[PDB]
Image: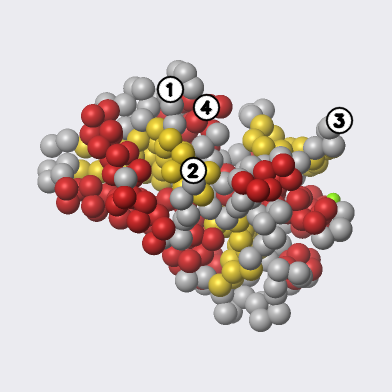
Amino acid sequence: GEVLTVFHAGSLSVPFEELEAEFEAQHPGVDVQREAAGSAQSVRKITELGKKADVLASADYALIPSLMVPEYADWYAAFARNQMILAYTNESKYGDEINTDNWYEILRRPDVRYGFSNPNDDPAGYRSQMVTQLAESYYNDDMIYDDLMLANTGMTLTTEENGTALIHVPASEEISPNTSKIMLRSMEVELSSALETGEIDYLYIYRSVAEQHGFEYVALPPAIDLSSLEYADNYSKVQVEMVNGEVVTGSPIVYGVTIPNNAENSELATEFVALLLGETGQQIFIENGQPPI
Ligand SMILES: [Mg+2]
Ligand SMILES: [Mg+2]
């Protein structure tokens, strides 16, 4: 029996589960086998750990050209967008009080705990940092990032000659989050249960995931939420440097997919990517809360 191995970002879990189901229905006998991990880590499984996949889907298309081309990939297709929000539930502390204008004041309260993923492994993780630093200029409060992140982790920040803020992420084992304030996981979707059970009050994550789980959420200003092409110039004012030296830049969230050039089942992969980009895939993404490009 043939097998199609798909490596994908954690946030793609729900829609990709549907694609696997539809693809398997259209291709009896073929077993689509998915493996999820933060996008940077999903890519490194291929580029550093010697693992092989037929399809690689990332929550940040830019990781394909920056990490895979041309040794492990030669192209990428942009197929969806997303938006960063602050998720919560009816049991989250101060949930009935939080809104777009005061979310960071609520997170500043000592009895409130928030979660975000590992910036060294997951776009949702480095994006939580980008959004929070961009919030300083938007709300005219130069201590939002300092208070929420620098004071509670091993991350550090420097200002570049061009005025760009550069966030430095230490080795994963050295991020050392203040556990009374932060819960960290390798990828964003690993924090869903923590939010649902109340171990954390707020969660930096994609709007699509919040909608899929039925979480409530605070919409953030488009100038800082990485959702719109219109604000691309503002988003680029922040960058994150991973422990390995790779630098990612604030940008509109665009998902990208590719077929590694060392894939074992490239032909089947082509049919899968065709389904993803086609009308059936498009519909699955929109029904799961992710707008097209
Ligand atoms: Mg399967
Ligand atoms: Mg600051």
Q: Is residue 43 above or below residue 200?
A: above
Q: Is residue 217 above or below residue 44?
A: below
* Cα distance between the residues tagged 4 and 1: 8 Å
At label 1, counting other C-alpha atoms closer than 10 Å, the crowd grade (few under 14, some 14-19, many 20 or more) is some
* Cα distance between the residues tagged 3 and 1: 33 Å
Left/right of residue 267 with respect to residue 200 in the rendered view:
left
> Can you say which quadrant of the picture contains the N terminus?
top left
- Nearest the viewer among 63 and 43 is 63
Determine whether label 2 and label 1 are within 8 Å by CB: no
Q: Position of residue 216 (x, y in %)?
A: 56, 72
Q: Position of residue 248 (x, y in %)?
A: 64, 35
Q: Quadrant of residue 232?
A: top right
In the rendered structure, which disc, 2 or 1, sits on the residue that comes first in sequence?
1
Q: Which residue is mark 4?
A: 65
* Cα distance between the residues tagged 2 and 3: 30 Å
* SS under mark 2: strand
Q: Which residue is mark 3?
A: 161
**Which amino acid lies under the numbered mark 3 shown in the image of this protein?**
Glu
Left/right of residue 109 with respect to residue 265 in the rendered view:
right
In the rendered structure, which disc, 3 or 4, sits on the residue that comes first in sequence?
4
